[PDB]
Image (cartoon, coloured by chain):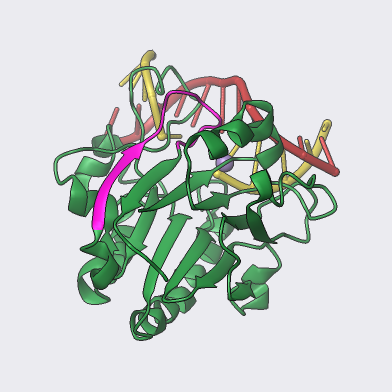
Chain colours: A green, B yellow, C red
Amino acid sequence: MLKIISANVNGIRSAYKKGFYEYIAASGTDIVCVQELKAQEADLSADMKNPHGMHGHWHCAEKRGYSGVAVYSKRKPDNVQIGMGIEEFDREGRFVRCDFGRLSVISLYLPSGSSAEERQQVKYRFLDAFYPMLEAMKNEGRDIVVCGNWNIAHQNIDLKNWKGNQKNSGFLPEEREWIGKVIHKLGWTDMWRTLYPDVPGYTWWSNRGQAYAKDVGWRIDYQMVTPELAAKAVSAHVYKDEKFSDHAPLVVEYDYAAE
DNA sequence: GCTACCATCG
DNA sequence: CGATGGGTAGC
Ligand SMILES: [Mn+2]
């Protein structure tokens, strides 16, 4: 049984403060994809690099206390790719790939364009140059999980107030259209949507108002899976027993064996 | 201090 | 629909 976790820690140090470290072991997971480390290698402790003896790898940004993704794994990954290859986005560190034989897990931090229009443009280009990547990986022949903060809502079911957010970044017709071109066109499987067609599955609630309390959140964290592995998925859930961050850890469980 | 990241109301 | 607001992490 292969348990994979995706979690935007929104600063890994705070998460470890709020008992995320302990949680990693408690969940008895085999792979953990974290987004937004908000730090650098020199900034992280040994436990934030190799939690509980679990191997680990990371991509950090040039900016201190900014962005950064990582992947922990009980098994020693055969190959590792830091950064997409596009320096423009690699200077922010949002892509980390780890091959574990037949399997390849990817931690992705899709840029959020809700801070400025220019950031929205950078996000758009990210999508444009990343689509071909999703396609190539779709045509490798290996089972590839993509855990990440896509920061894009697909349908009206993926967010509580889908009605008053069409003029807001994250639910813009363009972005949603891209996602569609990924699931149906590219042939990826929205693991959660495929396991639970009627469950909202919110994974993020804004600090504004009392949203988190009223379960007024979005679903911006995805695990896009290849058909072969997609079918092998047995369950999934959004862990909320403890709040480590404004995001909630997506825990998917597959009946897979990379060996 | 500066940077980055929409729910409730008028 | 449009006008009108917010608290986080980390340097
Ligand atoms: Mn964040």
Say whether residue A181 is visible: no
Is A186 inside the magenta-drawn segment?
Answer: no
Q: What's the residue at 34%, 84% (across, down)?
A: A141
Magenta stretch bounds: A233-248
Q: Quadrant of residue A250?
A: top left
Q: Quadrant of residue A83?
A: bottom right
Q: Is residue A151 left or right of residue A50?
A: left
Residue closest to the eye, A194 or A134: A194
Height in image: A70 above or below A182? above
Q: Is residue A100 left or right of residue A229?
A: right
Residue A22 rendering spot, x and y as whole percentages: 60, 32
Height in image: A11 above or below A85? above
Residue closest to the eye, A250 or A47: A47
Q: What's the residue at 15%, 46% (across, down)?
A: A197
- The quadrant of the rendering that contains the C terminus of chain A is bottom left
Height in image: A186 above or below A166? below
Residue A211 rendering spot, x and y as whole percentages: 40, 22
